[PDB]
Image (cartoon, coloured by chain):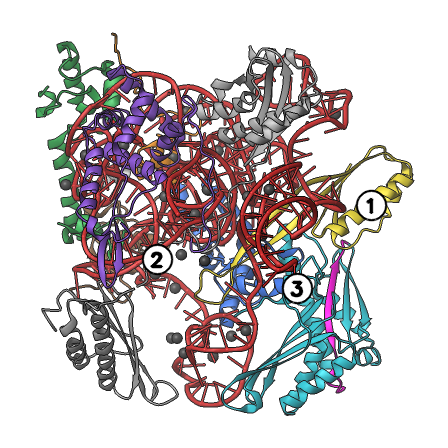
Amino acid sequence: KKNPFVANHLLRKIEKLNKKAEKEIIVTWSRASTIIPTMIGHTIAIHNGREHLPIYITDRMVGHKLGEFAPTLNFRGH
Amino acid sequence: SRRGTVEEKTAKSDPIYRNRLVNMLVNRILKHGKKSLAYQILYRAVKKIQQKTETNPLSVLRQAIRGVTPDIAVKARRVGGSTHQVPIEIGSTQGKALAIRWLLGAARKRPGRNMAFKLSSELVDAAKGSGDAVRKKEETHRMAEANRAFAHFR
Amino acid sequence: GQKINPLGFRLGTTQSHYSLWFSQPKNYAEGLQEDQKIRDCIKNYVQKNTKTSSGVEGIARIEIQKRIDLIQVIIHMGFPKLLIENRPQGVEDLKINVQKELNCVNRKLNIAITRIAKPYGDPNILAEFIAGQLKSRVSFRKAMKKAIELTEQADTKGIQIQIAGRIDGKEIARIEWIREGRVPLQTIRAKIDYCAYTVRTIYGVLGIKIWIFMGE
Amino acid sequence: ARKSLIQREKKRRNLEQKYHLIRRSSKQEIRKVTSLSDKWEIHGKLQSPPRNSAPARLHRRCFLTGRPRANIRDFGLSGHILREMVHTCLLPGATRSSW
Amino acid sequence: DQVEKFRKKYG
Amino acid sequence: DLEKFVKSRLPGGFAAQTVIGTGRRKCAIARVVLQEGTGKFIINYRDAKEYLQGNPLWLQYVKTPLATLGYETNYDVFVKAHGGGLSGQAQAISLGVARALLKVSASHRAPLKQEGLLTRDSRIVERKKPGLKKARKAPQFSKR
Amino acid sequence: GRGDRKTAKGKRFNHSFGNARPKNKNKGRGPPKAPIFPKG
Amino acid sequence: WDGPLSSVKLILQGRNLEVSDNVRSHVEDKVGKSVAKHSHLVREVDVRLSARGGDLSKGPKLRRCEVTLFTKRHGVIRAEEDAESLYSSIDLVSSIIQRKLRKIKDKVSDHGRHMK
Amino acid sequence: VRVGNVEIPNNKRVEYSLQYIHGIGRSRARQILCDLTLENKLTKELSEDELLQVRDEVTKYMIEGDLRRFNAIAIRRLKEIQCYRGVRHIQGLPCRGQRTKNNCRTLKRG
Amino acid sequence: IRIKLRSYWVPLIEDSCKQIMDAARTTNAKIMGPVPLPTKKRIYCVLKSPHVHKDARFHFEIRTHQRLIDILYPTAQTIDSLMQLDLPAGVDVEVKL
RNA sequence: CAACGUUGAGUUUGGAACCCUGAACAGACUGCCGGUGAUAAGCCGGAGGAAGGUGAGGAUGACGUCAAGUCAUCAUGCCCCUUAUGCCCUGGGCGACACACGUGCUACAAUGGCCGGGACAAAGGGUCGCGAUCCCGCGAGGGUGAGCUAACCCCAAAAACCCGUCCUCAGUUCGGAUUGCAGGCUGCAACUCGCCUGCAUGAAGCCGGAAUCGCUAGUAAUCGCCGGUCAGCCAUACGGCGGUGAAUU
Ligand SMILES: [Mg+2]
Ligand SMILES: [Mg+2]
Ligand SMILES: [Mg+2]
Ligand SMILES: [Mg+2]
Ligand SMILES: [Mg+2]
Ligand SMILES: [Mg+2]
Ligand SMILES: [Mg+2]
Ligand SMILES: [Mg+2]
Ligand SMILES: [Mg+2]
Ligand SMILES: [Mg+2]
Ligand SMILES: [Mg+2]
Ligand SMILES: [Mg+2]
Ligand SMILES: [Mg+2]
Ligand SMILES: [Mg+2]
Ligand SMILES: [Mg+2]
Ligand SMILES: [Mg+2]
Ligand SMILES: [Mg+2]
Ligand SMILES: [Mg+2]
Ligand SMILES: [Mg+2]
Ligand SMILES: [Mg+2]
Ligand SMILES: [Mg+2]
Ligand SMILES: [Mg+2]
Ligand SMILES: [Mg+2]
Ligand SMILES: [Mg+2]
Ligand SMILES: [Mg+2]
Ligand SMILES: [Mg+2]
Ligand SMILES: [Mg+2]
Ligand SMILES: [Mg+2]
Ligand SMILES: [Mg+2]
């Protein structure tokens, strides 16, 4: 009843890579945009602020955002 | 208070019974300035005390307070490097204060259901000389008299 | 302790305002902005055109009154021998620039210059004077005393002068001040003229505050 | 503050002027017109104009200094300069007020 | 099912 | 019903009538019309006990200016009020009544001054002062 | 309780007028607490 | 640091400086001596270190230590020291604390016959 | 009465008794009671006819077992997902964007 | 015709009112008086210092006073006598017709 | 103020007699009387008076102290960087988390909590704005859009309080943390990190050790309402406003 969200550039990239039927890594900064069904099985590398982190997309992911899967904070221990 | 002393404030009267006394009690029972509620509590207390006994509650006030009024207490003095409990005698206003207070405290600690009921119960017990508010005063007297030797102004 | 700018302390009592206009709260910001732009311009212009011809230019203050039609700038000034005598009289030469700045739509501008008769009974002027003498590396004692002299021979009831900074280029800063006559700062009924000025020397900045008391 | 900040602000004002009516237009377009898979594309129009074009991006700074905090709107001045000016009587109608 | 769950909301 | 008793008893609005008094205390203002006969307390088109809730206190403030006199069955009081709370409105009623009474007969003076019903209670709310929690209340404070 | 966003109080404190604390007399409150039948 | 002082809070704060292990230990020692003997009264020990001069700022190389004590009954024991080395500074603060402390113990804990 | 979903409302008003099922708060309570069944009394004073209706209605709303496994599979899923909230659940740190520097104590007691 | 004066300082506004009222009293038109409207008064508080101290505050207001002037019957001479008027630079006038 | 009738009212009458608004003016000065006091300043009392001894609050802060705070509001001596210590952008970060220290809010219940029905404020803000009415939603909200540049219209529901009905002692109809589900709004964008709603969840916690803080009257306590910042907000904060209203020297 209101649109979900995804970055334009991201959307059309996924369009092209879907049509040409190859699995290529996608470096993206959109830490907001939702994972819509038509991207599943792709590998997307999301910006953690320094590095891109490769994530494999799955059936489960859909309905969340991208940034849930790239932890921004480096913490192990006191 | 180092300089100024205190002027006297108009002693009011309770609306129904036109007493200085009852008015004193409703002011000390008061919390969060709801006078509206405090009057209700005090009057349903007069109603439970006229319920249980056929004696005039106006008088049961005089007995409840005459019962708990301490004529003496102690005070801690620093005398010659020695800390004494010196049994200072109490003024009348202070007596009535103390009284209503121990009454109210012993009334707030009761096991019962309402505040009206509690207050009534303790008014009944204090008028009979049968309760904590009285016991408290007798303790203050016990611990005054043991220390009777330290009042040099005797 | 801190005092209050004794100006701001009598406001709507013994002292007027300077900007005399009104505006609806929304426009108020814009209007404020506008005053600032012209006060800036008119300060600059005169500074450069008089200090080129080498004189002491008291610009004592600037009153601005906005009316729906015409906005009027009244310059209180101590010696307009440097603004009038020049061929393009300050009136026109400024009228043009100031009218460039504010706008010309629904607003046309008028400039009027007023001669403040006793220049040393005005703090602002006096302070600029001491500023000149100190910029000239005269010792501050002399400066202070000359100022006191000029003023008291210029008709004044009381004056308090304060100079703060690295005085005489000495490495540790300090505060020197002189009271003369009678300066009530706490009496609201007292007509008090204060002013604050800043000075740029080889050794850094120097503050001057001047208080002047004109009676009750 | 930094002159560069003030400049950032100015260029923002300019861009927002340029794209203003376009914003209102695409906005009423996405508000009023249904079809989710259409609203994809009109949201694709939305995301095109520069980020420095959104009203949300603007920030008021005191027009005299430019300090980013503490600006009361009526004057467009920061607290401090506002105080000074109230003492030199440049604010018409300002009075140290005690109620 | 999170794909169909997503398509029931939007479609 | 009571609106017609008030209206029919009083044609001239609240201003015209000979005997009127005005209470004000805190933010409450009350205008008071005094009349002769029976005794009825109508405040803002409702009853005394209806409005003031029958908090014995407030009622007693209202009736107190006539108990120094004993005119309880001799006068009829119609007042309008606004502002503040009912306690204050009551106090106000009290005062305006007293002023009305001094308007009818001046002989009342000495009782009313001995009771102290004639004075404007000046005590009002104090403003909140910067750095403080409310009025005189200072925030919880650590010596360290 | 003042920290309960499920109550008239709590809503009033949180400045959210919502199901419990309705804007007008025509906005639906929670399902009714009306029936009790004491007779005696 | 001490167990008999376990009831005491040792709070050690560099203001402009970085705190080492030798400063740690040294603080525990010198404050340890002062506090250990009067431990029944003592409550919280607040030590701040401030460095200045040399390469940091203008003026001599000053290192300045401030300590503060609190006792169960008496509040406010304040001591301020300026010196060359952190170590020196600390030694000084200890010298002062000791004195003020035993002045308090002296006052109240003497059964002083104070008649008046 | 017991049979309401293996649990025991005891000797109270019906609503506040119904609530003791994990799965019923205030809303479902007074809705079921004052809308569908229509009667309000004590618990043991419930006539058989009423009690039956009650059981049959409450049976169509989720309950302790089914809810518990419902939310548990929720949480589990999130944990499998390796998303943020999952990470937080697994670690035992608060997920609703509440600060960790000071007060977590409720969730940190675990 | 009704005129709403609004201005900051008082003397200015009632002298201005006085001009209007006398210049309309002269031209023989009836006036419903210079009716005072409630003074609208705005408060701002600010931090005294540039840094730190949160407690030193400064209170300043802006008071705005409103006068109302009801002229009953709009003669040609009345409208002109009041359209001519010289009202000081610190007052605002609104004309509702 | 009254009237006509209406819940939309009118601008529809009269009154200026109450109230209110805001401008001018008067009033309080130990001024009068008595008692005290060297006569003196004054101090205890009494009258009148709305107010009586700075009537009550506010702004007001001397010479100076702390080489107090601030070169990150602004200004500036000198020093230093100048294909970088300057500048543009998107992501991060200032929101981490074994802990410790300080300020607050809510609580631990019948002086109470829930529900239903009634009553009384103040002062504010509001044309890119506040938004009545009606309609859809359990609900945030959505659609509609009068009226208002504000003593006119709106935010707007004042809440404690009261009259009734339930619980009358429980870890409960106390208390509401935490978490899941499903939503709403702002805004290109709500995952890190917004706020709000509906259903569910129902932790601690039975008045708190040593110690310690605020307060002398419209004060404490207790109850809500507004504002500034502001697209939205972390506001329980800050600045204000009134409601109820103590004890003690
Ligand atoms: Mg003495
Ligand atoms: Mg000074
Ligand atoms: Mg700069
Ligand atoms: Mg912003
Ligand atoms: Mg006030
Ligand atoms: Mg208050
Ligand atoms: Mg504070
Ligand atoms: Mg507050
Ligand atoms: Mg509850
Ligand atoms: Mg909130
Ligand atoms: Mg809501
Ligand atoms: Mg509806
Ligand atoms: Mg009329
Ligand atoms: Mg007297
Ligand atoms: Mg005074
Ligand atoms: Mg220093
Ligand atoms: Mg520093
Ligand atoms: Mg610099
Ligand atoms: Mg850098
Ligand atoms: Mg960035
Ligand atoms: Mg921070
Ligand atoms: Mg973070
Ligand atoms: Mg808080
Ligand atoms: Mg606002
Ligand atoms: Mg709406
Ligand atoms: Mg427990
Ligand atoms: Mg209990
Ligand atoms: Mg204290
Ligand atoms: Mg806001």
Mark 1 or 3, closer to the camera: 3
Q: CA distance from mark 3 to mark 2?
A: 36 Å
Among the chains pictured, the one given green colouring is: I
Under mark 2, the amino acid is Phe
Q: Residue at x 66, y 64 (%)?
A: C187
**Location of mark 3 (residue):** C187
Please, what is the three-letter code of the amino acid marked with disc 1?
Lys
On screen, residue B58 versus residue D86, left or right, reads left
Q: Which residue is mark 1?
A: J18
Q: Colour of chain B?
A: purple
Q: Colour of chain A?
A: brown
| Residue I65: x %, y % from top left | 10, 32
Residue interval drawn in magenta: C50-68
Q: CA distance from mark 1 to mark 2?
A: 57 Å
Give residue B8's position: percent from left, percent from top: 46, 41
Amino acid at the residue labelled 3: Thr
C67 magenta-colored:
yes
Residue B47 at x, y percent in the picture: 31, 18
Q: Position of residue D62 (x, y in %)?
A: 54, 63
Q: Residue at x 62, y 24 (%)?
A: F32
Give a yes or no on whether discs 1 and 3 share a subunit.
no
As measured in the structure, the alpha-carbon distance from the residue carrying label 1 to the one carrying label 3 is: 33 Å
Q: Which chain is orange?
A: G
The dot on residue F141 is: 2
